[PDB]
Amino acid sequence: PLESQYQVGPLLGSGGFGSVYSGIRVSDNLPVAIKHVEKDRISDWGELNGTRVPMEVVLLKKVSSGFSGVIRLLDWFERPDSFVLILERPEPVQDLFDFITERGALQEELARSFFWQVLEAVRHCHNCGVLHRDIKDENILIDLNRGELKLIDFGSGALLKDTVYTDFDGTRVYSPPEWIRYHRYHGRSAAVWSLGILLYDMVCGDIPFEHDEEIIGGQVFFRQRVSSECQHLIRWCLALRPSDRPTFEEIQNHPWMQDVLLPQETAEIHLH
Amino acid sequence: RKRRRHPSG
Ligand SMILES: O=C(O)c1c[nH]c2ccc(Br)cc12
């Protein structure tokens, strides 16, 4: 039973991802997050034993093998009108959107560390056959003591494929111009676009584009002092033509990405 | 300049 295994705490948030409560696993006081998703809102479904579960459960299981920069699904339950997902909860934690709001534009050394860990997390998803489709600062949690970033909210994701995607329910201001223009995109190159938006967000303090005309226009104005190397990487990730964007390997080999801090160094220098 | 969250799903 779900009610006897977990002590439920305050609501942490609610939105397109459902309703998420703080919780504690009774058997060992492990901090958890308890996420409720209404069945009537689940668009894409999957099978595990063939049990019909939300695709989000399928994707979380595929990536929750071992230790990584992805939120770990510990358990899940079916209720009459909803599914309940138990996720491991870092503590203390702050999501990257609130972090950037409070700190402003991030020093490039800190943006490099954060961006590197997000790249490693997204590579892990893709290695496991999972496309997140909603990479953004709001969907990244910072473990403030360990200096580790965790990707959350796979509810807009999909199985990774090499053919074209023609559906999308992620965040429009992180979506690529080929989606805006043609309602078509491929998984990896669209992911790289959202990563370019995320990196601009980190080093400038907010995302570059709010409107469709800006997304498709292909001009990146820098509102903060940003190094030439970082600017080049951002503009490369935000190439209008998807085939002009870097691979994950080219991103991580980029000159701006070298000499990344370890997670614990990042915490000690920037977070503690 | 107004920074805001953006919905998804
Ligand atoms: O607080 C929120 O809005 C959250 C949404 N999805 C989550 C997954 C794990 C944790 Br911890 C928190 C959330």
Image (cartoon, coloured by chain):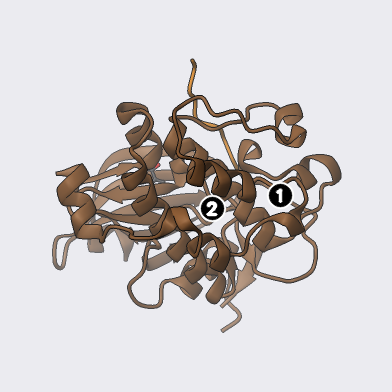
Amino acid found under the numbered disc labelled 2: Asp
* Image spot of residue A269 (x, y percent): 17, 47
The chain carrying label 2 is: A
Q: Which residue is mark 2?
A: A81
Q: Secondary structure at mark 2?
A: loop
The chain carrying label 1 is: A
Task: Indicate left or right for A75 with A57 as reference.
Answer: left
Task: Name the residue rendered at 62%, 50% in the picture.
Answer: A237
Going from N to C along the chain, the mark reached first, 1 or 2, is: 2
* Image spot of residue A10 (x, y percent): 26, 39
When the figure is inspected, residue A76 is found, relative to residue A181, above or below; the finding is: below
When the figure is inspected, residue A234 is found, relative to residue A58, above or below; the finding is: above
Task: Name the residue rendered at 60%, 28% in the picture.
Answer: A221
Task: Name the residue rendered at 45%, 42% in the picture.
Answer: A137
Q: Is residue A254 visible?
A: yes
When the figure is inspected, residue A99 is found, relative to residue A255, above or below; the finding is: above
Amino acid found under the numbered disc labelled 1: Phe
Chain B rendering hue: orange
* Image spot of residue A84 (x, y percent): 43, 57
Chain A rendering hue: brown
Q: Which residue is mark 1?
A: A168
Q: Is residue A43 visible?
A: no
